Length: 228
Ligand code: NA
Ligand code: NA
Ligand code: NA
Image (cartoon, rainbow, N blue to C red; front, side, top):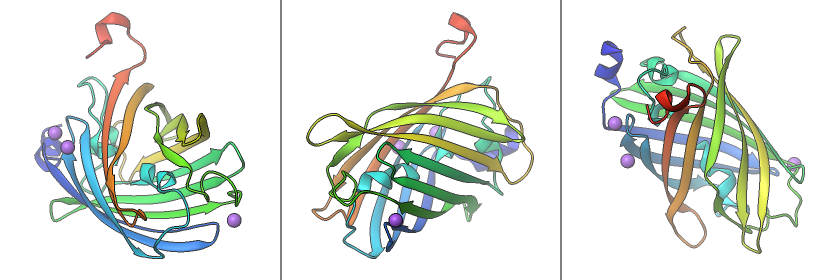
């Protein structure tokens, strides 16, 4: 929309704060990021500010650090962009295959021309000798999130696959609800294709940089809607 393209510029910065705990270990992270919301790309630079070094895999946190930066076809309402400047909230559950659980709540707003993200995380039930608490993971596979409208919100479901250092994958089933603070136009069902990379980190993962690409694609409509 015109007013929304006026405030969600083609280059946007963000600030983020997470406070969480994993298996009872409390921590805080601050970060800053930047990206191109209409091109689907962003980077972030995170710093552990309390509770470091973290005694678990950074990879369970990386997907919690920004769907305002999803490239959308013009004919798919970009609900999360349209939610600004008030913004949106999201809530997520991740069920990992060994019984570990992460749940997340998040607030996204726009202040002084930058996005402001506030993340709260609670991770529980990870086995002590499992890949999360033993730091045996090596980043996510690319993922397609199946998006669909329901009861006034946007929901996404995905199977995320964490690569394991000794081979194979450690899987999570994930469901997220995204809901604008004000009613704006919901899309139909479509897919968000994501690739999230850790581009650098220090030895103990107290300093981390990430890159993600996110693009919405039609899942119906055939060749006409392919690459729209
Ligand atoms: Na970028
Ligand atoms: Na852009
Ligand atoms: Na626990």
